[PDB]
Image (cartoon, rainbow, N blue to C red):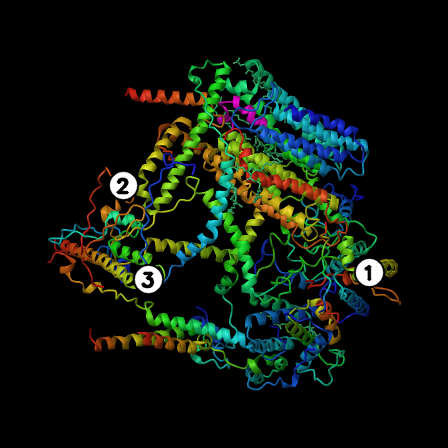
Amino acid sequence: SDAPPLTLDGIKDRVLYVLKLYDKIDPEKLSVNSHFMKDLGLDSLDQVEIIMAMEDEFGFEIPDIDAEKLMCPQEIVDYIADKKDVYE
Amino acid sequence: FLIALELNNLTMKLSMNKANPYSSFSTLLGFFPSIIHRITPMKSLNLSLKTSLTL
Amino acid sequence: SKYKPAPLATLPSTLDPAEYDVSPETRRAQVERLSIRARLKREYLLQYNDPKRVSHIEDPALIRWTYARSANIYPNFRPTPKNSLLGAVAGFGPLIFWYYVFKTDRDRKERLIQEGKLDRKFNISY
Amino acid sequence: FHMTKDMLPGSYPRTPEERAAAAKKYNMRVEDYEPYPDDGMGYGDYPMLPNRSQHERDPWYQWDHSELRMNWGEPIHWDLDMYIRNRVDTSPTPVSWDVMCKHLFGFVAFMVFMFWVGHVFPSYQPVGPKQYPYNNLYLERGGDPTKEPEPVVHYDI
Amino acid sequence: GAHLTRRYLWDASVEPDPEKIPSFPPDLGFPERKERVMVATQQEMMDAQLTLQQRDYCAHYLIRLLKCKRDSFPNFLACKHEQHDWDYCEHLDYVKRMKEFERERRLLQRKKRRALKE
Amino acid sequence: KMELPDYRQWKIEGTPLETVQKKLAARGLRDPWARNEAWRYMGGFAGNITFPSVILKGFKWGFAAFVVALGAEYFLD
Amino acid sequence: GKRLFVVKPSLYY
Amino acid sequence: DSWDKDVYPEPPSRTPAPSPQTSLPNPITYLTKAYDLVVDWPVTLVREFIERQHAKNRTYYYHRQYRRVPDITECKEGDVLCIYEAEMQWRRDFKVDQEIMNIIQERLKACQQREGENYQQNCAKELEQFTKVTKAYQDRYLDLGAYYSARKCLAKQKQRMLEERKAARQ
Amino acid sequence: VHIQPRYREFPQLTRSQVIQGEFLSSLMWFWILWRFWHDSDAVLGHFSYPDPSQWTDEELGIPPD
Amino acid sequence: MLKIILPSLMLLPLTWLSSPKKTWTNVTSYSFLISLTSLTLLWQTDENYKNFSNMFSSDPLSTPLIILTAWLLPLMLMASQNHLKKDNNVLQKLYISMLISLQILLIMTFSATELIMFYILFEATLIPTLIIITRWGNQTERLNAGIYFLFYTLIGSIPLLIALILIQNHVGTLNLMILSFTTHTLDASWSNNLLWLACMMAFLIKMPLYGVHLWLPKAHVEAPIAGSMILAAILLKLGSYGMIRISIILDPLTKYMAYPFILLSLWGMIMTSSICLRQTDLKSLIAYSSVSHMALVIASIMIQTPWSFMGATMLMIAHGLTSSLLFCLANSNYERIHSRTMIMARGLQMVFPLMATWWLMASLANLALPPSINLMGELFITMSLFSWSNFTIILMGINIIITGMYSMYMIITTQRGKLTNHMINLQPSHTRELTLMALHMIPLILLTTSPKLITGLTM
Amino acid sequence: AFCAPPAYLTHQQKVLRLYKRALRHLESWCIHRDKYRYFACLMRARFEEHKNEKDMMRATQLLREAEEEFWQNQHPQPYIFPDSPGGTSFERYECYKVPEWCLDYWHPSEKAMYPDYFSKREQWKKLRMESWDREVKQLQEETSPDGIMTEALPPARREGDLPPLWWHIVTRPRERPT
Amino acid sequence: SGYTPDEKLRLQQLRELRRRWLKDQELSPREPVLPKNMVFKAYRSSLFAVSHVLIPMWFVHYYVKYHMATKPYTIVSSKPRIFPGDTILETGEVIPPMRDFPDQHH
Amino acid sequence: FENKVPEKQKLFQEDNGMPVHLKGGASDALLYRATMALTLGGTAYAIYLLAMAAFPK
Ligand SMILES: CCCCCCCCCCCCCCCCCC(=O)OC[C@H](COP(=O)([O-])OCC[N+](C)(C)C)OC(=O)CCCCCCCCCCCCCCCCC
Ligand SMILES: CCCCCCCCCCCCCCCCCC(=O)OC[C@H](COP(=O)(O)OCCN)OC(=O)CCCCCCCCCCCCCCCCC
């Protein structure tokens, strides 16, 4: 009925959607495993805004310690899938 | 209705205002829940344990 | 324009002055605090995740707290002037006060019944 | 079980060796451990944990006792049954405690004073009393039929 | 209204409180004041069961309204004419009370004028 | 599966987000979340909802039913 | 579809 | 009905005649006629079946009566036999008086519910009867204690007679 | 009953909900204007509160001077 | 009464001659038969008390206590037959013999027409509950707790004995009905005050009155489940029954000698309910709740009003039933977790839905939910106390507020909340203990339906 | 939640935490999205223009002053996510997250109601036993004899091995169990 | 900073075993192994009215007549309203009307 | 009586587009709203009163 379940592909597509809509990340160099400082050229404040945007997009917040551990969309996807128990 | 409409238009208007004790009093429920629900159970349970049972 | 704390509204850990003037002694003190916390967490996690465990995990903290709150009080009690005065007032003062108010109330009631100025309307089942 | 007197709580510590033994028993550091003052209230060597409720503890941390927000083996406050999350909170407030007390007392006293002001200065309508017939309803309110009341007479205007 | 302002700001001697109404004898200024009369009596009021608050001088209009309701219980939007009649009688009683109040206010002013003339 | 819209449609023109963007560029700052936040002002969400349009919803149909009812009452009486 | 097993205590007793 | 109007008085009902001024039908009358036909008829039919079974098996029971033993005033003190007999008599009369007060209270409740908003005037005789029996009950049975007894009631009555005799001197 | 979820555009509006909503709103407004036309006693009543100052001393029954 | 006394006596050869695999079944079934036989004392068509013999009688006050004891004995065997499975056959039969002997002596105690016989059977009931609490208790201080219980009761009971032989010498027979008829008014001297205190302090000790109540909480902590039942459901009510029977010959000076104990009871129920708020032990918390309810019973009996006597009688029966039920719930949790700490097991509403329902119903009975006999007794005690003095209503209000608070705190911290997931040793439910819970609650429902059986002497 | 906190919070961690909390309270005050975006850009500009600080004592002073300003200007009722602590829906389904060990205590009738699931459960328990013995050995090897110890746990360092203390993470109940 | 390689490798192993546990939480198609409609007005709203309403009506009407009206003061009601111009059904008199209403303004 | 003009001045050169007659916060906005509702409310009362005088009873 209501509240359709999440998928791994859906989570990946939504986080890539948000990162594509972010301006300092040009969408052509963006990958699922692109690091924020190594090959994306961001900093800690940019990671903070990215994390809060993912929280606002998915409706749940990430605690501060896990949020500062997440550093690229691959473990962003992994954290969201683990917290919402999305296995397939 | 018109006063609250105007006020909501002011909140729509792009400007931050300084918070005031009137709105703090209204938002924190008149401070009755925090103040009473902290000062009455603490004194009651402290009187209970530190006088009745123990003493 | 300063936040003033209370025992019932404590001061925030991000607003205390004791953190911004931090010292290597305090830093290492928190380091062994984390070490003890991690040791206790590891012991409880091992006992929790043992599949051969067939009973509840006993808690020495709970046992010590229960004995301290139940059985240690009279072995560790020493009579002082202060606790003797406090025990005397807390065991007698309410009794004397309630005795006085009950005695005046009942004396007024009995005298009013005796000399007739209190009229019972329909008090038939007392 | 296997609980003995040496790690069970005991008497008030006097020597630094006894204080260190008590700290080791309670799983605290020697400098962090502080017993209650020796005023003979039966506290013994139980530590003076800070008087903060369990709401101060980190809610995102996976505590061993999740309802209590406490780990396993750490010392328990003497007033845990006061400071559980179902009971007395000591959390920081967005405004000061004295400010909240002053504002609440001021609001209550202000309302009481203006209620007294409105009581001594009541508001009404420019009318007389309500007009009622038959000696202001003498018989229907339960008057004695044998005893004739004073004639309450009303006139047109 | 303005009566409260004149009582609590200007003067309280000429502005009267609503409890000692009347404070003057009815024969003063009325050479022949007739007694008030009502249609309903105690027997029919008791039979039709009016509460003691509503046993005023519009009891007969109240009885016709209640008889209207009890007869035409279906189509409750049919008692409007005698509902308006009872309301108009209540208006007459209320303006009679206002007449009484305004009369004793002017009588208090007349007494103050007599005191000043003395 | 749930197909996603094309993110490149989330442009920025005709929007209070460009009102904010012009105000920031006057000060000299850039907002990188404008395209992410621009979906709430485009498409079916693009419209100024007003209190007359909220309370007076269905008022013209209510007025039509009201005048038809008056015509029926006048024809009956 | 996608029915998931729900964890319940032993209500049989 | 096992009750009677001698001890449960009730004025005769005065219902008014229906005068439907409107032309609409009465759903109350329609529903009560339908309800009668669908519910009251089978209920009364099975009730007459049960009552004819009762008439086939009719039995009788009697209201027990106790003779008047001599009162405690002529009982010698310490002679526990006659004291026990008078005490049981006093307890039975106590229970009878309790049920009498229950009857009076039920009568007062019935008066108030029947009169409604006219209870201040029409229930004057019932309230007066309740006041009289209340005063008599207070004078005979009040303040006896949990261990109320015929001896305690007699002591209270003797004290009341002495005080009213001293009041009657002047 | 069931409808598809859509990511960032306006959802599809079924006919049942919109027609029933406008029907309820129009019913409310029709009722308000109907009662306001027939019994408009929400304003002023229909009773016309008199002015006490224009009342005369002869009908008020005060002695002249 | 002999038709109930003799087969209860013959239960002991049944216990000691039954097969080891049939002893519990035989004794439970025949003790249920004993309860059904004891139900015949409710045939009261008139005020003549059922004086069956020259030494035994039945009374509207004595009958509910006898029926409660005869009903509680099979429930005692049910509750105690699980923690004795890892035990010797002779010791199991000995424990069954102790329970049966208690039940016999309590029936004779409540049916005795003689106060000397009442005292003899009083100490006769004092003995085997000591044996139970001392031999079958669990941890160390069962012995010292039994020492408090025994010597509080004995120092209470000795001046009662001295006053009993003094009253016998003054009057002649000490029979209850003869005293009730030839009651003599005391001349209010200091010797009469001392006589009153001597014949009152035994029941004041074993109620327990506040300040002398120190034996009860540690005894209920340290006792087995049948010991907790016997104390908190029968023995306090025995003290109150003795108070009611002895108070008839103490007029008039009880009206002013009742002053300190009424105050002691009111302040005691308030402070013990505060302890129940701040108490970390479940069994001791129930014990302090029992102290508060028995303080209410003292207040009613000392103000000595007919409503007070009715309220005392219903509070006796209702509190006995609900305290046994609460102790059964605490015992079931105790055999699950091998601990008595109140905070250790929290989310039991998850694993045990029906047991949490029994918990809720027991606590609702405890906090005086209408229309139960708990609130009937409490409300009639409140009305009689307000008749005695209008200012008792403040103390009543404080006591009722804290009573509801500790009952709902019990439910919240023992059933509701997150489950302690480390508690692997949580067996689902025993049909035995669930049957015990039902056999506790259903008589409460029946007595709620018909409260006329437990009215008492007055009305 | 999935990462244990360290002994102390670094200055960068405190600055980032204050930045996130200030932005959350900013959106709670601002409500409207364009207003929030404007003032969030302003706050980001403030943090950027205090970013390049070299003294670090003035940086700690600036952090303390910013914390005082935040505590003075914070929303009395900030926006909280429903699953966040203090939220409306927080701990709502703790009454439904039943632990996995009652399935052992289930009756054989309820065992037979779900055969394949219980076969998989027995397979998981056997794997748990073997991995438990191996990971007890691994955790005994990995623990330093003396020195600093953190709450983090090592992974499995060879093939066919499971990470130590994996059971209460892997077999934890679902956050939406029903 | 980001994930340390100790936690980074650990988490991917814990996540991998989490997917296996959640996949095993699914049910096979045979789970669980368990051991005249007409229309709503004609059937569904009909038998409920004749069973849960009509049968309890018979038992209640049996109680309120043969066990309530037989008791003295069970069902007691206020006297009905009697207006002028009405006729009593029980006794038979006509209540006399009111006076002339001297005021006929509205 | 201290000098707070220069702090009050910088509450008047905000280039937010808010006009000078509403730049003083919310209090002047409420004063604006109250005077706008009460001159017009007075005006409608005056026109009604002039009409009532022009058409006598
Ligand atoms: C459990 C509570 C324990 C403490 C309180 C105990 C009761 C206190 C009040 C009663 C007095 C003591 C018991 C007397 C029993 C008999 C009473 C009686 O018959 O009275 C009438 C009799 C009087 O007899 P009489 O009424 O025939 O007198 C003749 C009168 N003429 C001549 C006019 C006809 O009173 C006594 O004999 C009382 C004397 C008691 C002397 C011995 C007391 C010893 C100590 C007692 C307490 C010890 C335990 C506690 C110690 C402290 C613990 C912390
Ligand atoms: C005497 C001392 C006892 C001490 C404890 C004894 C324990 C062992 C008990 C063994 C069995 C003995 C039971 C004794 C009571 C039995 C109840 C009973 O049948 O009472 C009689 C009653 C009819 O009596 P009646 O005269 O009509 O009532 C007074 C009116 N003048 O009958 C009835 O009304 C019918 C009763 C059965 C029908 C079902 C009733 C269901 C009630 C549901 C109540 C719901 C609310 C509960 C609230 C609880 C709150 C905590």
Q: How many marks?
A: 3
Q: Which residues are magenta?
A: J241-259
- The alpha-carbon separation of the residues under discs 3 and 2 comes to 41 Å
Q: Sort mark 3 into few (<14), some (14-19) or many (20+) by Cα contacts within 10 Å.
A: some
Which image quarter is the N terminus of chain K in? bottom right
Label 2: state its secondary structure.
Answer: loop
The residue carrying mark 2 is D143
Viewer can see residue E91: yes
Q: Sort mark 2 into few (<14), some (14-19) or many (20+) by Cα contacts within 10 Å.
A: some
> Could you say which quadrant of the image residue D10 lies in?
top right
> Could you say which quadrant of the image residue L20 lies in?
bottom right
Viewer can see residue B10: no
Mark 1 chain:
K
**Circles 2 and 1 on the same subunit:** no
Q: Tell whether position J111 is magenta.
A: no
Percent of width and height locating residue M56: 20, 75
Amino acid type assigned to the residue bearing label 2 in the image: Gly
Q: Residue at x 54, y 20 (%)?
A: J177
Q: Is residue H32 left or right of residue I62?
A: right
Amino acid type assigned to the residue bearing label 1 in the image: Ser
Q: Is residue K174 left or right of residue H126?
A: right
Mark 3 chain:
H
Disc 2 and disc 1 in contact, CB within 8 angstroms: no
> Could you say which quadrant of the image residue I33 lies in?
bottom left
The residue carrying mark 3 is H22
Percent of width and height locating residue F69: 37, 75
Q: Residue at x 44, y 40 (%)?
A: L70
The residue carrying mark 1 is K119
- The alpha-carbon separation of the residues under discs 2 and 1 comes to 89 Å
Disc 3 and disc 2 in contact, CB within 8 angstroms: no
Which mark lies nearer to you, 1 or 3? 3
